[PDB]
Image (tube, helix red, strand yellow):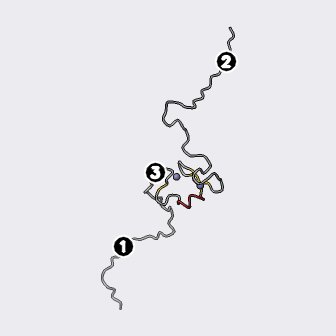
Amino acid sequence: MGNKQAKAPESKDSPRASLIPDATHLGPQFCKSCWFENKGLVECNNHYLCLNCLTLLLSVSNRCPICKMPLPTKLRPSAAPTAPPTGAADSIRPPPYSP
Ligand SMILES: [Zn+2]
Ligand SMILES: [Zn+2]
């Protein structure tokens, strides 16, 4: 008869299952908002914007419009150059005798 292995790849160009068939959640390394360039590209969490246009609209002065998500929370500075100990065990209220 002629037994041979056959190949059958699936184009899957337009699938009708899974609403987000895309498996990308980071973004390409090319800024598509202001223009194509790699001089100062910065990768947002789920979005890509370069510093050149990022400064004009700020990274997130109020909200990132491309991420389509609000961020009212803030990130702590994670720094503490000053942190002396305190306790004030000695009670204070009356004036000093001052001999
Ligand atoms: Zn840009
Ligand atoms: Zn963003």
Q: Which residue is found at the position 60% from the left and 51% from the top?
A: 31
Real-space Cα separation, disc 1 to disc 2, in angstroms: 87 Å
Residue indicated by mark 1: 89
Disc 3 packing (10 Å; few <14; some 14–19; many ≥20)? few
> Where is 35 relative to 24, above or below?
below
Disc 1 packing (10 Å; few <14; some 14–19; many ≥20)? few
Residue indicated by mark 3: 69
Image check: 86 left or right of 56?
A: left
Which residue is at the front of the view, 74 or 93?
A: 74
> The disc labelled 2 sits on which kind of residue?
Gln
Q: From the image, which quarter does the C terminus lie in?
A: bottom left
> The disc labelled 3 sits on which kind of residue?
Met
Q: Which mark is residue 35?
A: none
**Residue 84, x across and y down, in percent:** 46, 71
Q: Which mark is residue 5?
A: 2
Dot 3: what SS? strand
